[PDB]
Length: 104
Length: 104
Length: 57
Length: 57
Ligand code: PBM
Ligand code: PBM
Image (cartoon, rainbow over all chains, first blue to last red; front, side, top):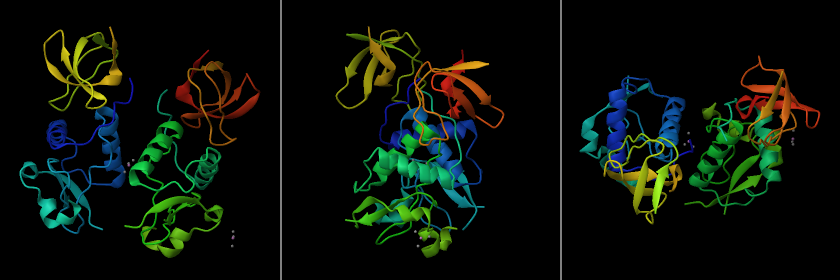
């Protein structure tokens, strides 16, 4: 089974992936780590073809908001120890672009 | 052609990869690009089994030194445009740790 | 020019088309990249498939 | 026992073992982990190899 063709992350792709993982009951609460996340990104990359360079969050401290509008996971402190926290409002409020309009 | 088994990075493996990639000349002077590098790292991950989280460089501006001791490449200017420059003495001097112990 | 699925594919996104090995497709769009827009001959369902997972019939 | 290569390999060091598809091997150790130490029957050289690239002869 070949590595799927590479493609850009999208708003719609980020919304489906978030709901899918939420269904899977994984990231919720899970303590964040570059390794765990790289593992995630690589899985999504292998499986769906979304190049592993989209899951960037905003600079801390506090909650880190996803730059990818449509990705419904934010990082909530619980270096701060962060936990992946689903928030469907991120599919409706591009917080990161307001806090840091420069990235866009 | 399966993704090779994972295997930890080690001074020796970083030193070996440096000379390996030097043999298959191509990085020299090649203009750096996170994408170009992400591609490189994924190739080594599938090919040789080194989880893509080793080739991290120090902050800018100026020359960006490799954080993994053994990796004999640094990013040299000409924001700031960078290139991959093989610097053999990086295997004998952990510059990145000297100048940026915060990452250690 | 029909195509046949060489492997199974399970979409997660909504615009992707899940399919099983042996399923046959008719490509609607293939110039927009390496993820083609295919129509299932079996179900009439349209969506994007990893072009590298299908081969001509 | 003897094993054979399903695909090629290209080592980045002399401590590992490069090879081609079909090369036979004598597994000198496989209790270290997933990268086995073996001897190429087709060259008479020892080095580590990705266990998943070789299958039993
Ligand atoms: C685990 Pb990556 C190729 C930013
Ligand atoms: C290449 Pb020196 C100054 C241990």
